[PDB]
Image (tube, coloured by chain):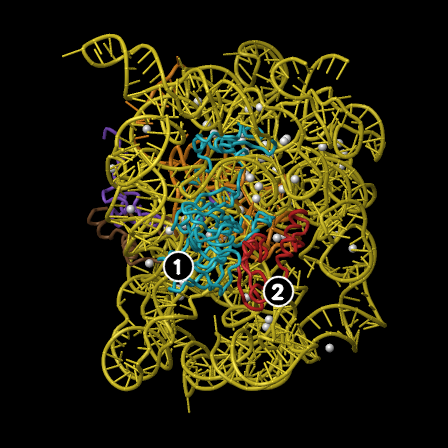
Chain colours: A red, B brown, C cyan, D purple, E orange, F yellow
Amino acid sequence: RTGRFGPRYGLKIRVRVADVEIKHKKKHKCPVCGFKKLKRAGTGIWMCGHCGYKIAGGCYQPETVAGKAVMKA
Amino acid sequence: GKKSKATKKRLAKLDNQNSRVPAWVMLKTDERNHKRRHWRRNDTDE
Amino acid sequence: GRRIQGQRRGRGTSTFRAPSHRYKADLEHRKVEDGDVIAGTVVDIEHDPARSAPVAAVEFEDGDRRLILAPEGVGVGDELQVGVDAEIAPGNTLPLAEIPEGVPVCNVESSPGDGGKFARASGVNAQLLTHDRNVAVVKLPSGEMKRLDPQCRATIGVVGGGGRTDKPFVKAGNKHHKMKARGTKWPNVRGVAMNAVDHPFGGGGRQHPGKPKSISRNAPPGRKVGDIASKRTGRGG
Amino acid sequence: TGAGTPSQGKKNTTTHTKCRRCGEKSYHTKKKVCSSCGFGKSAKRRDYEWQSKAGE
RNA sequence: GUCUGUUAGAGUUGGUGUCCUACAAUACCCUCUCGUGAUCUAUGUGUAGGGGUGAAAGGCCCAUCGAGUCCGGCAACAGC
RNA sequence: CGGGUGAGAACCCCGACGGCCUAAUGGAUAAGGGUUCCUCAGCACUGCUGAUCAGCUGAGGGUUAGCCGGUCCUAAGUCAUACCGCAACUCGACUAUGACGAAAUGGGAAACGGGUUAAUAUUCCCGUGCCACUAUGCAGUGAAAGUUGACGCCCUGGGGUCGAUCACGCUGGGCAUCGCCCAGUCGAACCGUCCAACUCCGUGGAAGCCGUAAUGGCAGGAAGCGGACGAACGGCGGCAUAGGGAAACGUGAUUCAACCUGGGGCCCAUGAAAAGACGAGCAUAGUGUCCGUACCGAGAACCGACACAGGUGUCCAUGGCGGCGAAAGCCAAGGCCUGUCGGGAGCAACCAACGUUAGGGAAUUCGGCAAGUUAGUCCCGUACCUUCGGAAGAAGGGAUGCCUGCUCCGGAACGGAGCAGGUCGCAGUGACUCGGAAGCUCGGACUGUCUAGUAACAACAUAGGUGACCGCAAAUCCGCAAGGACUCGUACGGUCACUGAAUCCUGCCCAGUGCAGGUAUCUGAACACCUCGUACAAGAGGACGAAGGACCUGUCAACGGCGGGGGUCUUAAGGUAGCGUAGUACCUUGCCGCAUCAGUAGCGGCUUGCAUGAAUGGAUUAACCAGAGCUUCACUGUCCCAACGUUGGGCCCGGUGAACUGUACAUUCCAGUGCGGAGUCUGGAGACACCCAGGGGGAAGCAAAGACCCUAUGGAGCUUUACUGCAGGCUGUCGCUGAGGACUCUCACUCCGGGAGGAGGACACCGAUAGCCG
Ligand SMILES: [Cl-]
Ligand SMILES: [Cl-]
Ligand SMILES: [Mg+2]
Ligand SMILES: [Mg+2]
Ligand SMILES: [Mg+2]
Ligand SMILES: [Mg+2]
Ligand SMILES: [Mg+2]
Ligand SMILES: [Mg+2]
Ligand SMILES: [Mg+2]
Ligand SMILES: [Mg+2]
Ligand SMILES: [Mg+2]
Ligand SMILES: [Mg+2]
Ligand SMILES: [Mg+2]
Ligand SMILES: [Mg+2]
Ligand SMILES: [Mg+2]
Ligand SMILES: [Mg+2]
Ligand SMILES: [Mg+2]
Ligand SMILES: [Mg+2]
Ligand SMILES: [Mg+2]
Ligand code: NA
Ligand code: NA
Ligand code: NA
Ligand code: NA
Ligand code: NA
Ligand SMILES: [Sr+2]
Ligand SMILES: [Sr+2]
Ligand SMILES: [Sr+2]
Ligand SMILES: [Sr+2]
Ligand SMILES: [Sr+2]
Ligand SMILES: [Sr+2]
Ligand SMILES: [Sr+2]
Ligand SMILES: [Sr+2]
Ligand SMILES: [Sr+2]
Ligand SMILES: [Sr+2]
Ligand SMILES: [Sr+2]
Ligand SMILES: [Sr+2]
Ligand SMILES: [Sr+2]
Ligand SMILES: [Sr+2]
Ligand SMILES: [Sr+2]
Ligand SMILES: [Sr+2]
Ligand SMILES: [Sr+2]
Ligand SMILES: [Sr+2]
Ligand SMILES: [Sr+2]
Ligand SMILES: [Sr+2]
Ligand SMILES: [Sr+2]
Ligand SMILES: [Sr+2]
Ligand SMILES: [Sr+2]
Ligand SMILES: [Sr+2]
Ligand SMILES: [Sr+2]
Ligand SMILES: [Sr+2]
Ligand SMILES: [Sr+2]
Ligand SMILES: [Sr+2]
Ligand SMILES: [Sr+2]
Ligand SMILES: [Sr+2]
Ligand SMILES: [Sr+2]
Ligand SMILES: [Sr+2]
């Protein structure tokens, strides 16, 4: 997480990078199969360690709040 | 540096041009190469 | 005085140009003879330098391989389609007319055939609202009600990379790296920190603009700086 | 670093060279233009009335 | 865009040291700062004078800059 | 110190002894130079002295390529032609085409080893090998899908060569109380062959096992077993009764640059293109042209006027000891005594750069400036504060060598961690290398930037905060135009500005100014229209009335403002939370306190603030800092107060050999005088001439037609509601421009579309003119 920043940058900034980076690196469930083996491969790019599936999605998380609206609409 | 065939002909000429005035010309003219040059003290074109 | 920076910009020198020779591809919609019948397969996902957002590489039936303005949710192997008879699913492209009201769209054309102009940035999206035989009302990311020709093509879904803005740059160095990929001169020196000869707000023993910051819209380039034709300023009121 | 002597040491770039058209060492090999006769820029020979006094 | 570091390399706080018809029209020595990054660097390439370029010092654009250099206007004008 | 050559020798050469250089003072090269390279003969010139020497002079000579570069390819980008613009071009943007653009250091068909010369050398020669094209013959009908060229940053595993080291053997050398020490022990390209990793297939059947340095893997089929594909500049065989060596002409090992092949992590950052190659056999033969090739590459061959202590790219980063080390120090290979004047004097004064100083210990000084103190490593231990990361190597304390014999970790190291006993010194990181520490306050959050050449900071930047403009036929900006940047961009964008991390917050004011919206009425130009005038025209007046203004409204994280009087007045409001004698407080060394023998300092408090105050941001703040101030401990020649010593100068001698400065005269001194600041005038005094050394009192010393100040109907940069104008924007009108105060239409014209056609439309664009802003 943010520990790599030491005492530089301050609370707010170090905190948000942590939040963002933790959700960012959680085990995410692959949409093709159902296994939570998704690791980010770059900005907005996600891939499944299991099925090899490669998807587009949020920058720091595979599904944006409004990315989910589309399914419904 | 690398010299082209032409640059070589020129440098070549500048070398020959850098000679003594024939001993005999000084007699014929009853008593200097004003274009005499030195590699270090002077600077050729190009 | 000397021309201000915004004037050096126009001359379009290297310092102010975008690294085009490093950019991948305009993501304008593919053109279809007609009757749709155009589908392709997503062969790979790539990073778009010019937009800090992912983009999809598609292989169409007729053997044409092109990068596409990818919405969120496109994955390798998936099948996309472009045409009127296109199935109303995320990643497909069809005239605003064939799109059901209430559906989120992106990369919307301004004029049928231009290949898309609106809603192409990360996570953004236009909401299609009204239909008709003459006009299709779309709500653009700025919240503006846009009246478009129902023949204007669009993609269903929101653009990939949402929330890119949620995370702070934290350090100048990070900013630096992104800037190095856009047509932008960075960092920024406040005009008020310049000599009078370099900018309207320059000079003075202590830094402070020597005039009100709200400039008229008819102000000439070189003088038009600060808050341009502002309708108001501040937060109060 | 001073602008004088220190900065002269960095000068080993070749620009002006013998010009195929006039023979002067004025052909800028990076610009490919003779600052003397204007070879590579003008089919006409580089002339200017200021190269001499106005009434001469 | 972490730390120590004369690794390479980049720089220069103090000595108001040495030098100041110099080794040098910006040099020498010790101390000092940076040294995985907004880093340093070679070559190539682009931007040109009321114009560039400038993390802005009116800084830099070949020892030249609050408007480069060359020649021309020109034998400028001055009540000094 | 000897000797050689020579007319002549400190510095040209030989030997011995003595030294210097180790990322360079060694090796190879790029740029640049251009013959500086080799030989002979010279010394008038050049050379910090001399010269027989030489980068100097004279005369000759020297650079050899199918396989090393160029050449070929394309990069940012450049030009030429066409098109269009421009009064015009040698000028100008776009779009087409073509070409150009990489010599160390992007891509790329092919060469190694040895020998040879005074000077060349993968080029000549010897041996061996390889590539391309073509021809012929055989084979082959496959031939273009695909692979390659072709790629970022960080961590890391495995394969593995050179090197280095260890063991033992062989050859040679050295030393001589010992028995150690040194060198060598060789051998390429190429041809063949082996294959780890990755990937995959068969078998198998794990429901907790497999695997790693780490992550990880699996019934969507783990381990195990077999198999396909498959690496090195690497191993092995040939090459090689080639070559090289006086000789021997090794074998094993460890650690392993190169090279090869994997695994992991990161991105608001995504890490070239093209030619070409493979895909696609073998023989034999022929062809392989053109250009570069010397030398230097630097404290003398480059740039800096110089044989300049400066500047100047690449690689040799694995030679030995040392140690963490590409550190110091010492030493090899290799190079050098040319960072090129010498000779004398215990060699004075004085200066540079140093060593050592008793007692005192910052008393010195603006200031501990300068110097010093501390120091490596291990163990113990470590405060306030804090954004919980840090602070922290806090502080403080202890240990440290050698020798003998061992233990533990590991496969092992010539790796690491410890134990017991012995023992020397004043001192064991013994040299070298190698932090002094602590507290308070101010500032900027931090890394970062800057005045090339007096400023490194508190200034600029920054992330973060905020406001503004714009839906893309946009906003902003460049161009006279043709056109263009932004833009392979589209509001999670990008333009224009302010503030400047985080934390707590950010009050009141729209009167003036600015911007914006609105507007009955008022005002508001030109064209057209009407009236008067004129046989016409000039002209006078009228009607209409765009933007603009008057008027109204909105807006201060717009410009800015938040006082004086009394218990409101100006000019809208009348200073809220904070903070406060401030980097802002004149008075001022404010008053009280702390600290000192004594404190215009510093800190804390008070605070009426001459003249603090909230994004002209306020307060506050951990971390950071060659930033400003203060205090303490430690230490010391900073000082009391100076001394002695070291090296280089200084002084004497040979040689070389300038410059600054010069109206004249000139041995001055004390007084006076004088345009009031005299070696030169007056009156006295003193004064024999010349030379050496010295520190600089005077010559209002020398240096630069004072930069301060004033003056000139001088100059320039900058400002603005100075004067006058010019671009630019907005707006009306005429032309383009057409049909049926308001409307429909299509046919010019505009934009979108490959096209059909679609959207718009007499508007807009463009040309002209007028009003406003400027
Ligand atoms: Cl950004
Ligand atoms: Cl691994
Ligand atoms: Mg932001
Ligand atoms: Mg700024
Ligand atoms: Mg300034
Ligand atoms: Mg200034
Ligand atoms: Mg200005
Ligand atoms: Mg400020
Ligand atoms: Mg300000
Ligand atoms: Mg040679
Ligand atoms: Mg020398
Ligand atoms: Mg005193
Ligand atoms: Mg063991
Ligand atoms: Mg203070
Ligand atoms: Mg700072
Ligand atoms: Mg300076
Ligand atoms: Mg900001
Ligand atoms: Mg406020
Ligand atoms: Mg003036
Ligand atoms: Na020369
Ligand atoms: Na000498
Ligand atoms: Na070593
Ligand atoms: Na106001
Ligand atoms: Na000026
Ligand atoms: Sr020179
Ligand atoms: Sr487009
Ligand atoms: Sr297009
Ligand atoms: Sr100002
Ligand atoms: Sr407010
Ligand atoms: Sr250079
Ligand atoms: Sr030309
Ligand atoms: Sr002419
Ligand atoms: Sr660092
Ligand atoms: Sr100083
Ligand atoms: Sr010193
Ligand atoms: Sr100086
Ligand atoms: Sr450091
Ligand atoms: Sr003149
Ligand atoms: Sr002589
Ligand atoms: Sr020589
Ligand atoms: Sr070429
Ligand atoms: Sr190359
Ligand atoms: Sr690198
Ligand atoms: Sr290894
Ligand atoms: Sr050579
Ligand atoms: Sr040098
Ligand atoms: Sr040696
Ligand atoms: Sr000499
Ligand atoms: Sr002693
Ligand atoms: Sr003191
Ligand atoms: Sr004192
Ligand atoms: Sr200690
Ligand atoms: Sr600088
Ligand atoms: Sr803040
Ligand atoms: Sr107002
Ligand atoms: Sr003297």
Q: Which mark is residue C8?
A: none
Residue F261 vertical placement versus F549 (above, below) = below
The amino acid type of the residue labelled 2 equals Lys
Q: What residue appears at the point 20 percent right and 47 percent down from the top-left corner?
A: B29
Q: Nearer the viewer, mark 2 or mark 1?
A: 1
Residue B12 visible in image: no
- The answer for how far apart the CA atoms under marks 2 and 1 are is 37 Å
Chain at numbered mark 2: A
Q: How many marks?
A: 2
Chain at numbered mark 1: C
Q: Which residue is mark 1?
A: C36
Is F637 in front, or is F601?
F601
Tell whether F304 sits left or right of F450.
left
Q: Which residue is mark 2?
A: A36
Q: What residue appears at the point 66 percent right and 47 percent down from the top-left corner?
A: A12
Residue F58 vertical placement versus F542 (above, below) = below
Tell whether C179 sits left or right of F81.
right
Label 2: few (<14), some (14–19) or many (≥20) C-alpha neighbours in 10 Å: some
Residue C11 visible in image: yes
